[PDB]
Amino acid sequence: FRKMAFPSGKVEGCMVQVTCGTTTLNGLWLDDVVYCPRHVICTSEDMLNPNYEDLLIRKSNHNFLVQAGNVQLRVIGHSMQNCVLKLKVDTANPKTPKYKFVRIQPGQTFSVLACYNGSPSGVYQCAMRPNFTIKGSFLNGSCGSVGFNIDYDCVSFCYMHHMELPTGVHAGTDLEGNFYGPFVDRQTAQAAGTDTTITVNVLAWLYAAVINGDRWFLNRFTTTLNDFNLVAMKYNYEPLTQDHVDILGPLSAQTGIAVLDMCASLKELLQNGMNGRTILGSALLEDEFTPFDVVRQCS
Amino acid sequence: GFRKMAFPSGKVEGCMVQVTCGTTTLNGLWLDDVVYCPRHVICTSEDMLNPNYEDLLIRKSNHNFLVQAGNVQLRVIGHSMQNCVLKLKVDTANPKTPKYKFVRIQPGQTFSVLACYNGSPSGVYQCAMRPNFTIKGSFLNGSCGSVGFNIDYDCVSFCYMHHMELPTGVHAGTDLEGNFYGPFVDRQTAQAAGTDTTITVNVLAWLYAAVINGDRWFLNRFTTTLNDFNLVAMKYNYEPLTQDHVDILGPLSAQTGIAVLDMCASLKELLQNGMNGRTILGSALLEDEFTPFDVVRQCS
Ligand SMILES: *[C@](O)(C(=O)NC1CC1)[C@H](C[C@@H]1CCNC1=O)NC(=O)[C@H](CC(C)C)NC(=O)OCC(C)(C)Sc1ccccc1
Ligand SMILES: *[C@](O)(C(=O)NC1CC1)[C@H](C[C@@H]1CCNC1=O)NC(=O)[C@H](CC(C)C)NC(=O)OCC(C)(C)Sc1ccccc1
Image (cartoon, rainbow over all chains, first blue to last red; front, side, top):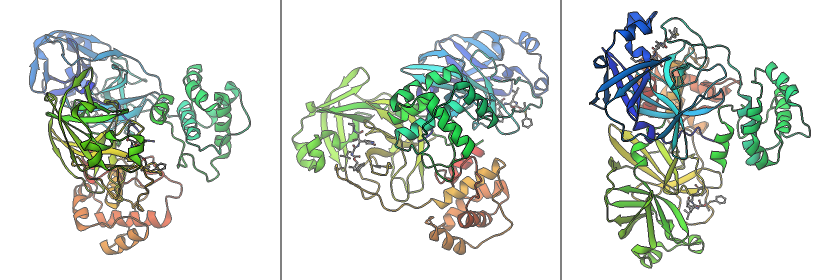
């Protein structure tokens, strides 16, 4: 199994750069609006403790330089929504795809198009961790890069990049400007909380192993959801939700293995270890492939 | 941070089309007024067992080829064969044609794959050309004709077109001149790859990446000569390291202050002792599909 990103072209066609003064971030151009992190309006001195409302009231449309490549896109309106700035522009992006803005849950995966000065550099798959960070790859200049999924022809934007934490993980907002996790857009010391293992994705991985004929770990027993969740937390595994049980349904139907029976197998693995064996050629249990990712790569 | 990262695929997406001959549908690459695709699109299931492609192709007419770019059929007005690739001349140029070239990559080099089904892009990921000339891709039925590429400035360098999956689950294909990487043939007959080796220069690059991201338990105070390292490498079915490789690792050596031969001494220790149940950059195995250039680009 490979981490596989969505093809990035539909998002590449929406990337722009936004400059205030000497500060250039990436923005997302959809119809006649450009979305970007509001900290583009901050000086280094503002960043230490910014008053965004005051900073913005002193800004005018003509202070914002929006460019697609080197072609300026004139700004005709501006507003702030949580931690994102929305700049109305006088040109509708002819490459706008069908799109929506979604807020994802921990454990869900998405593709990141890393961009610098509006120019795409690379694309990779990420999982939202339970502590609301992503293990991304981002350098200075990447703020405003977005994460997304593509369903049929519709791009669901779910992430806009803002922050790199001391442990080298990343934090950001949805496209309505609300941070995932407790983070704030201020240049003050912050840290990722203790992370946990994404149980629903580990289960998806076990289902993937079964689909490929690797099934030594299946046992004759079952468990209740509550008993499993209480045990899982003692191994720093996330508890399951009803939604997790639901999204495992297709894999459960494909293999004939009830979700709670697979939970009982995973519990035995947690309690007893791998005893030197591998699953899908790995001694480690993978937790960044969702049930959707598994069906998309097996079938 | 450090991720396996593919090139943005947009420039290639705008070239993907669907090609159907008989009951076989796969992908084609539409550049200017030519569509490139695997020649086995012309085979029936019976032909595939032992195809005489020149004989099979002369019996085909332009109208036997259905090319579709989205909702639009493209009229085939000419066809020819170059090794294992079929070239369909069509009556309209692709306005989305990027600046491009066709290159043949060397083992150990990386490239991005745009996996496509029925002419539609489905996913993108990074692969390396293995020393045994396979690639460890993720390809299903319908993926034939998907391509691999690198991007340099605004120029797309196409290096791979997908043809086959071997019994071990690894993959095989051609350059865009239709010549296979490796000893493989486009016939439906069981085929095995030669023994593979690990791409040593890439393992070292990835160890340098691990240091840049603060993961350095595997370092040691020792050093080694290049030849003594290579003796151990070959014993463990790792490729030998050349002085060109040492030079290419230079910037990573400069960035970290770890001499290349010192990192070789660390890798020697890992080969001889294993990882003692530890991990590097989250992996329990030594990763060899990041080139030095891949690492520098990401960690600059
Ligand atoms: C983003 O602002 C950006 O790319 N701006 C472009 C250059 C003008 C950067 C992206 C970061 C920089 C390095 N890698 C990245 O992904 N974002 C920021 O610099 C953050 C801006 C805030 C949100 C207003 N600031 C930031 O991430 O600082 C981290 C701290 C201070 C919150 S936590 C920390 C403390 C000590 C050491 C490391 C991290
Ligand atoms: C390609 O032809 C394609 O996608 N065609 C579309 C569906 C009409 C496929 C791609 C393969 C299919 C499964 N995963 C893939 O990457 N290519 C082929 O089917 C090969 C066609 C040849 C080149 C004429 N055939 C093939 O890959 O078979 C493998 C063997 C027979 C060479 S080796 C083998 C033997 C036993 C078990 C597994 C593999």
